[PDB]
Image (spheres, helix red, strand yellow):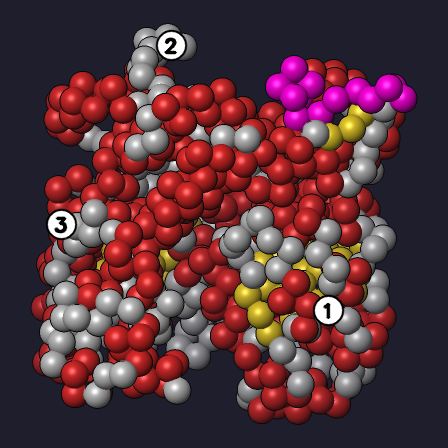
Amino acid sequence: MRVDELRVDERIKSTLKERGIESFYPPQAEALKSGILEGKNALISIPTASGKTLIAEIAMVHRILTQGGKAVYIVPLKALAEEKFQEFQDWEKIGLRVAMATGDYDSKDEWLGKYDIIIATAEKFDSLLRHGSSWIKDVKILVADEIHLIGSRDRGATLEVILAHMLGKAQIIGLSATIGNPEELAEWLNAELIVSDWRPVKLRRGVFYQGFVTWEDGSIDRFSSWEELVYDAIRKKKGALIFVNMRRKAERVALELSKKVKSLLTKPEIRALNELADSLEENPTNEKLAKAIRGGVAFHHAGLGRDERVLVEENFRKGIIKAVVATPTLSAGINTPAFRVIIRDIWRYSDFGMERIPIIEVHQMLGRAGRPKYDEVGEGIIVSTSDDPREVMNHYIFGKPEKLFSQLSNESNLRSQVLALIATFGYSTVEEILKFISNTFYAYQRKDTYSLEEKIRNILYFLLENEFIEISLEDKIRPLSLGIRTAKLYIDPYTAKMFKDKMEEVVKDPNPIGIFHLISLTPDITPFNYSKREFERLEEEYYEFKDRLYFDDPYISGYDPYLERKFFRAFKTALVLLAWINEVPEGEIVEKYSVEPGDIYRIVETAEWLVYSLKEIAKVLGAYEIVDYLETLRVRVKYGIREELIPLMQLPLVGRRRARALYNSGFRSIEDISQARPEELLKIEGIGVKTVEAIFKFLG
């Protein structure tokens, strides 16, 4: 169907046409005519290549243009908010303001009140709901992108909860991959179900095994090695996307490929890759990237800094970079299909131990093959090495995706969610809590929820004994300041407990390493990892700074190589964080502590939040003597600077490096910068035109 067959506000039609959208794929047409334009809930389970976002965009905008109010778009990862923010930009042209809200959990963010479209993670939205932001009542529709994640252990419960809170309160639309129990999820969501396998480009799926690829139709094609699949694609002026389990494997395979790909590149292509390879800021992780890119092959994984990942994704989308070997974590950042998708690993290091990559993910990966503009057929190939090809074919290609199970039993999320109910949602009796539970997806899939109930009852004990809540004289369950504060900070009650239990120590010896180590031991952060060769040096430094730690014994819970590792991981993290506030250049940190740019950015952001949370728990506990210290530390962690640079960080385009160059040249305050001649800032090594322009604009 065409845009003009669409029964929506004409200002939407104009925007679509202006984007070059004239018609809709069959799956989209079915969805648009399912009732969502009328306010009905819906679960859209179709290929990613078939444009799920557009369907949601139309539904959201149409919803608020007719009923006014707001639309909330729930993105899976905060690093994905930006992209959505950019593509939602043209809605500003018809008077709809778009905003990104993904951090600062301890805020009502009332400033979002004047916006119409709000992009945020499930956690951020959960957080806002707890704070009771005055604009929440304004939300008419919430879109849960990659809603199948509700079945994921780590964060699925949070998505389930915000859905439970919003159901019946706003229209709910889910964008989902293919699953095993489509109707069960739709039923719980009181939604219309749209299930389709239609895609714009035919997808051919097969399994590669010892020299041959056997396609799902039974035919065979010879390829001496799996990499020939990549060379063949490039030889055909098309591209390839290779998926691997580990970061180091991603890089090693990228270099290997690039070694044979370079000789398949035109003279220009080679010079274009060079200009690109040259622009990568000096750095170990970036050194490998540049060297591989000069061959037409890049690697993609969370260790790379945002800028580097953007470069790789955009140039892959431009066909400059011919192939990309990437990991799972942020592969969603690469929004560009590829003629061929090669799944190199089908087993991944698991927690308890190795396990097969879920069928759901394998299907999502294969569904990335076939570019609409260049391909008439996309090929998704599963590489089997240790597995029987017929078994792999039967399991992944012929078999059905796994059913999604609620992950509400997660002790981490459940303790946080049970406290949140009492501390921010007014739940005061066990019966009421179980009432909320009876409306969860968890309960929906079950005949009974006896164990969860026993699990909740014990959580209440934990909260009572630890003083987050209390039983009033009325025999009701009520929160205490510690509890309310913990709920709003969004930290797990366990990390709050840790902060409370070690507060007396922090007060006695307020110091960086100890604080950074303490927070790095909490469930709310993922510390840096370390290789075996690093341990000896880590151990030495540990003894050196042992007396500054609040958690000193590496084995208070056993000798499990897992627990000793956890402790030292937190310790190494504390060391990196100290270098960070001591203004050691990123390149030097990456190099000296064997950590990656992407991880530094992530840990720094999380640390700022946790140091802030520690400051706030110190407040509720009355440990006011360390609040100023903690507040200052928080800001130092936020920017990676010494206390004296703080006054300059409010400046546009000014980071730790520029603040330093400014300060050392005599511009220490906004006042010094205010009375400066542009030439005075331009002489400073590090400050360029665009920076002075932004600074002078900022100042007037």
Contact, mark 2 vs mark 3 (Cβ under 8 Å): no
> What whole-number distance in Å separates the C-alpha atoms at marks 1 and 3?
45 Å
Residue 468 within the magenta-colored segment of the rendering: yes
> What is the quadrant of the N terminus in the image?
bottom right
Q: In this figure, which residue is indicated by the disc labeled 2?
A: 556
Three-letter code for the amino acid on which mark 1 is drawn: Lys
Say which quarter of the image contains residue 388. top left
User: Which residue is painted at 21% across and 47% down in the image?
Assistant: 582
Mark identifier at residue 53: none
Give the left or right position of residue 74, taking residue 579 as reference.
right
Q: Is disc 3 placed on a helix, strand or loop? A: helix
Three-letter code for the amino acid on which mark 2 is drawn: Ile
Q: Which residues are magenta?
A: 463-475
- The location of residue 326, given as percent across then percent down, is 32, 53
Q: Is disc 1 placed on a helix, strand or loop? A: strand
- The location of residue 465, given as percent across then percent down, is 65, 15
User: Which residue is painted at 36% across and 23% down in the image?
Assistant: 508
Give the left or right position of residue 287, taking residue 343 as reference.
left
Q: In this figure, which residue is indicated by the disc labeled 1?
A: 70
> What whole-number distance in Å separates the C-alpha atoms at marks 2 and 1?
50 Å
